[PDB]
Image (cartoon, rainbow, N blue to C red; front, side, top):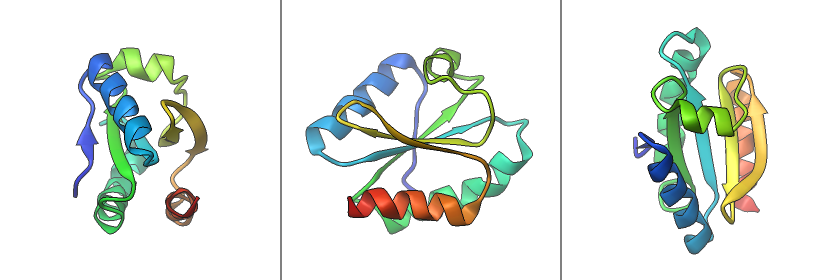
Length: 111
């Protein structure tokens, strides 16, 4: 896919600012290597990044690799998906439903 891997708070801030400047929504997958359903839904997140390439920005945050971002985002259960617009959180979805992830991305690609 074209998912962007976040490796630091500085990278996070730069991506959120990019989505603001471009007026494109950002969808973020908060994931962990130990999370079974996270690994199950990762292929779909990749496919969606291709399907919406150029329209929606896709980010990935490994919560243990970038704990400062996971903490600031208030993560507690996984998978968690966030949508950012204008640099701030606009929507979220917690859980491994593939139908619901598809619907979240479709809603913001059309909004």
